[PDB]
């Protein structure tokens, strides 16, 4: 994994989940 998610992958992160934001 690469970012925050449901499914932990390697290291400490999960998926590269599509976290698009503004505010």
Image: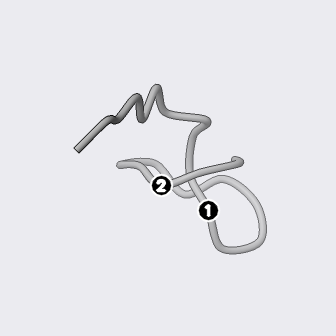
* Label 2 element class: loop
Q: Which comes sooner in the sequence, label 2 or label 1?
A: 2
From what the image shows, is residue 12 above or below residue 6? below
From what the image shows, is residue 10 above or below residue 14? below
> Is 5 on the left or on the right of 22, as rendered?
right
Q: Residues within 10 Å of mark 1 (few under 14, many from 20)?
A: some
Residue 8, image x and y in percent? 54, 57
Q: How many marks?
A: 2
Residue 9, image x and y in percent? 66, 53
> Is 22 on the left or on the right of 10, as rendered?
left
From what the image shows, is residue 8 above or below residue 2? below
From what the image shows, is residue 8 above or below residue 12? above
**Among all residues in the image, which is located at the extreme front?**
23
At x 59% / y 51%, what residue is drawn?
3
At x 46% / y 48%, what residue is drawn?
7
Question: In the depicted view, which residue is nearer to us: 3 or 19?
Answer: 19
**Among all residues in the image, which is located at the extreme left?**
23
**Among all residues in the image, which is located at the extreme right?**
11
Q: Residues within 10 Å of mark 2 (few under 14, many from 20)?
A: some
Residue 1: image tag: none
At x 22% / y 44%, what residue is drawn?
23
The part of the image, by quadrant, that contains residue 22 is: top left
* Label 1 element class: loop
Distance between mark 2 and mark 1 Cα atoms:
6 Å
Residue 13, image x and y in percent? 61, 62
Question: In the depicted view, which residue is nearer to us: 21 or 7?
Answer: 21
Residue picked out by circle 2: 4
| Mark 2–mark 1 CB contact (< 8 Å) | yes
> Is 16 on the left or on the right of 4, as rendered?
right
Residue picked out by circle 1: 13
């Amino acid at each position: 994994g690469l970012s925050q998610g449901v499914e932990p992958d390697i290291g400490q992160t999960y998926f590269e989940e599509s976290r698009i934001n503004q505010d």
